[PDB]
Image (spheres, rainbow, N blue to C red):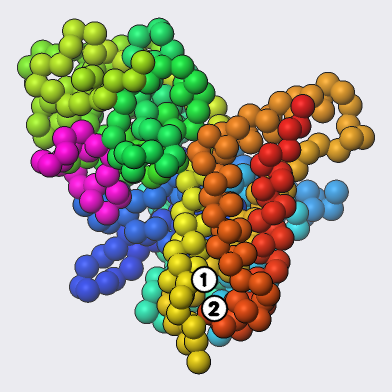
Amino acid sequence: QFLRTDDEVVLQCSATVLKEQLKLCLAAEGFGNRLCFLEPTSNAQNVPPDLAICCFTLEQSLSVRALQEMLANHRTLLYGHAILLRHAHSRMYLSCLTTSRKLAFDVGLQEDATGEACWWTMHPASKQRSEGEKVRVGDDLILVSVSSERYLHLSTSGELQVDASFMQTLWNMNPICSCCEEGYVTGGHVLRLFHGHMDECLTISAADSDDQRRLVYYERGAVCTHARSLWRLEPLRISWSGSHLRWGQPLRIRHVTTGRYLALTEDQGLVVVDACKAHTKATSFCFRVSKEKLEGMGPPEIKYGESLCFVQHVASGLWLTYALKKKAILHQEGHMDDALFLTRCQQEESQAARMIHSTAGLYNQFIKGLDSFSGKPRGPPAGPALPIEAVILSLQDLIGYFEPPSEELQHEEKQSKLRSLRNRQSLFQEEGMLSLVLNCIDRLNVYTTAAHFAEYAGEEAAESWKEIVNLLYELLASLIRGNR
């Protein structure tokens, strides 16, 4: 009934578009782009929203005097309290930025929780709540930046955005999960699906495969530690999507590094499909106890490791089965040994897998823009603008991410940090990040100078040509660095 600290939440607002209400969640990537944006959730039945980057953790909830004393150097939320919100993926903190996209400031994530910028005071939306009262689940609230004294605001030229404005917006701090039972599978969890005990898991193929990475397999060996075998369980009901999963409950299964959804198609059978084509009927599955014919955290039913689960496609009733590497299919009978167990991926690996997803998406966009004016000069590029700012920041972020530990650190800590670095390098390497970085280099090296690049791209885009190539070479080096 009440919101507490260390609860996972989403910040939701609503807007009227085409005489219909549209629910929107506060989202940010962090790496490559600090700025917050809005992720629509109303059309979930047709197109699944990108929720992994919508999740925030309530770090602290402090009174006015408690904040002031903290700046000089599980608790229930009360009105008047100032809260610190940590982004689940990037590990960064929601803040009011000093830059502007009007007397509004931009809203985004910052690297460190220092100063007032990352603090937001909670205020009642009506006379039904008062200062010092317990913040209840489902309450509309007003959020005020401690630094700028402005409201967290839904802005509208023709797009729906977030900023810090003197205009008010009502926000719903919807709980994703609360204290949940240990060892139980919940929504939003990133995991692996294992078949037997021979190091065999459900996966798509490696990068650059003739597959186009659309097919699903049972694969043995090194896959079991690679990013390509990681999946995100996404229940159809957005409310309490981070609640315990139940037998028979419909859910979508998202592939982390590609962002594609397990689906049944009329033409291809069992494949993995783009988000835009991942509608309920094709993409909805459930865990079953057997093959017999058939608003809170809820009852805990599915255990990690100990529970054996059959995967069923809901609309068709077909079972997930196999055709070492065996193709995964959907079949009316399947096989007697179809039952799978689940194992929870830890945060370093899951974080890395999402970073790869966004990194791949961004640089592939950058590559597509480069190919757009490949043999087309200007007298007016005139294709879509290259994501210069995002590419630069992405590059800088990954370089810092792959930075070796300081030689001044102690041996025990250094070795552990080196081991973590190697594992993180490996996950990127196995997802074809070297080739991808190289493809950017090779395409930019087609040009001899910045001025030559300006003859095909813009003069403004050419201003960052030398910087991007140098940062790419730097990332390339950091991806290879042995770090033994």
Q: Distance between the residues labelled 2 and 1?
A: 9 Å
Question: Is 189 positioned to the left or the right of 317 in the image?
Answer: right
Label 2, residues with CA under 10 Å away: few <14, some 14-19, many ≥20: many
User: Foreground: 455 or 283?
Assistant: 455
In the rendered image of this protein, does residue 455 appear above or below residue 117? below
Is residue 276 within the magenta segment?
yes
Q: Name the residue under label 2.
A: 457
Q: Earlier in the sequence, mark 2 or mark 1?
A: 1
Q: Locate residue 430 relative to residue 484 in the image: left or right.
A: left
168 or 214: nearer the eye? Answer: 214
The type of residue carrying mark 1 is Leu
Looking at the image, residue 20 sits to the left or right of residue 433; the answer is left
Q: What stretch is highlighted in magenta?
A: 263-281
Is residue 212 shown in magenta? no
Q: Residue at x 84, y 53 (%)?
A: 72
Q: Residue 328 carries which label?
A: none
Residue 298, position as x, y percentages in the image: 33, 27
